[PDB]
Amino acid sequence: RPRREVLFFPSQVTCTEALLQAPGCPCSLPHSESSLSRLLRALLAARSSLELCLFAFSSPQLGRAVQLLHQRGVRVRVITDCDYMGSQIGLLRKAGIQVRHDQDLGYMHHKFAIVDKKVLITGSLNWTTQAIQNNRENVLIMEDTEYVRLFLEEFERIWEEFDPT
Amino acid sequence: RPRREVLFFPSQVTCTEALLQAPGCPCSLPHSESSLSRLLRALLAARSSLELCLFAFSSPQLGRAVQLLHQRGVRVRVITDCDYMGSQIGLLRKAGIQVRHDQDLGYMHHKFAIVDKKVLITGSLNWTTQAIQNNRENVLIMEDTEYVRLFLEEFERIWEEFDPT
Ligand SMILES: [Zn+2]
Ligand SMILES: [Zn+2]
């Protein structure tokens, strides 16, 4: 019953235009699933809340997904290692998504996301196009109440530590 | 019944001299458990096989643990991103442990270990003293037959790809 998946990267290059509600498919890419499309779908399943705790976040596809969730009324909170001050984090911040951050020293090295306080997405993968398309990486997607509890506790500790006020 | 733990880092600094069978405790460090001691114990529980697939590996404590397992007759196979050509990987290689490697370009970005084809240890953590003592990181320790199967399959694919012959 409970979701337990693992995605291995590098991801196959596939079309995500419909998934990401592209404005305006006739493209040449495969229209089938990949590790990236599976990750996107896990995130886009969010109806209530998304916590993101990511060392690095520059993927425009993943940025678009998070944008759409914010536009849908999902409560999005993001922690990254760098403040990123046309970056994705810059665009998320401009859209009104709360982003808190570390010293850009390497210290905040988690790569996880929590969807609706019920699904934990966690791996070796930094959310960058370079890593997604080129690196050997893993991302776990788990509906596990204890892991979600413990990761949400960690998230909230880091969230409060980085409160700009 | 099945093990499902998560270790969060940075690790408390605690004594590991007895655990790592130090030659020759009167030290000033706490003699209690930490995220690092828990990781060490998970590895040292190996009786048969250890597969390590690690972006970076420079921790002398973790190096010592792997050494001891090799000396105990455990079948140790290591994949790292860099060839490391007094490094830990150098010392493991000299001791007769088979190490295979990537291009030192960032591509081999996993941070996992498989103990006795039954426990998967996987996280955000690179096995370096700097990361262990300073970074916010997670390491999962899971007795999960499907995750172990799929991670062992991935390991073997990478192992064969990097066969020096
Ligand atoms: Zn298309
Ligand atoms: Zn001691």
Image (cartoon, coloured by chain):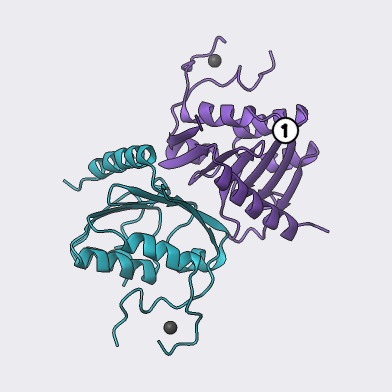
Chain colours: A purple, B cyan
Q: In the image, is B79 to the left or to the right of A83?
A: left
Secondary structure category for the residue under label 1:
loop
Front in this rendered view, residue A89 or B57: B57
Could you tell me which residue is drawn at 43 percent across and 35 percent down? Answer: A10
Q: In the image, is A162 to the left or to the right of B65?
A: right
Residue B141 seen in the figure: yes
Q: Mark 1 is on which residue type?
A: Ser
- Compared to residue B128, the image places residue A1 above or below, namely above
The image position of residue A96, as x and y in percent, is 81, 39
Quarter of the rendering occupied by the C terminus of chain B: top left
Ligand 2 found in image quarter: bottom left
Extreme residue in the left direction: B165
Chain letter for mark 1: A
The image position of residue B35, as x and y in percent, is 49, 64
Could you tell me which residue is drawn at 26 percent across and 40 percent down? Answer: B161
Could you tell me which residue is drawn at 74 percent across and 32 percent down? Answer: A74
Front in this rendered view, residue B9 or A137: B9
Label 1 crowd bin: few (<14), some (14–19), many (20+), radius 10 Å: some
Front in this rendered view, residue B37 or B81: B37
Could you tell me which residue is drawn at 35 percent across and 42 percent down? Answer: B148
Extreme residue in the top direction: A26
